[PDB]
Image: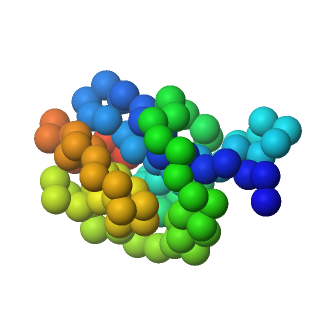
Amino acid sequence: PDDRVYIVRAQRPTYVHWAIRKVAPDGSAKQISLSRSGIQALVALEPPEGEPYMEILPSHWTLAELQLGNKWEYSATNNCTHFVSSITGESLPNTGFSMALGIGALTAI
């Protein structure tokens, strides 16, 4: 019940990565966003990366965690901003796609 959950923002070289992070009382953290396996984008845990942008509800974590391993169809109009916004209801600037790299910008697992 003491877990805190945030939208986090990580500036990457070609685009802005958005994620959801859960921080435990002991300061350990988990983070979910979009990654890829080869050419397949997907929802995945990732190392905590980036700066807290906005605190949100614990229930938002559950929504993200329930999507782990789902496929994602990655595009200019469907990227990490949309993943986070669809969970949280928060508007984020559509900064979350790399025109130069497209899906290549996502971290490989």
Query: Which of the two residues, 29 or 69, is positioned nearer the viewer here?
Result: 29
Q: Is residue 39 visible?
A: no
Q: Is residue 26 visible?
A: yes
Q: Looking at the image, how many numbered discs can be counted on the residues?
A: 0
Q: Which percent across, then down, holds residue 59?
A: 60, 67
Residue under the point 32% across and 41% down = 105
Query: Which of the two residues, 79 or 1, is positioned nearer the viewer here?
Result: 1
Quarter of the image that includes the N terminus: bottom right
Residue under the point 28% across and 52% down = 91
Q: Which percent across, then down, holds residue 5?
A: 61, 50
Q: Is residue 25 above or below residue 59?
A: above
Query: Which of the two residues, 42 or 91, is positioned nearer the viewer here?
Result: 91
Residue under the point 31% across and 25% down = 13
Residue under the point 30% across and 59% down = 82
Could you tell whether 20 is left or right of 62 in the image? left
Could you tell whether 76 is left or right of 4 in the image? left
Q: Is residue 11 above or below residue 25?
A: above
User: Residue 28 appears in which quarter of the rendering?
Assistant: top right
Query: Which of the two residues, 33 or 63, is positioned nearer the viewer here?
Result: 63
User: Residue 84 appears in which quarter of the rendering?
Assistant: bottom left
Q: Which percent across, then down, holds residue 58?
A: 63, 60
Q: Which percent across, then down, holds residue 107?
A: 44, 44
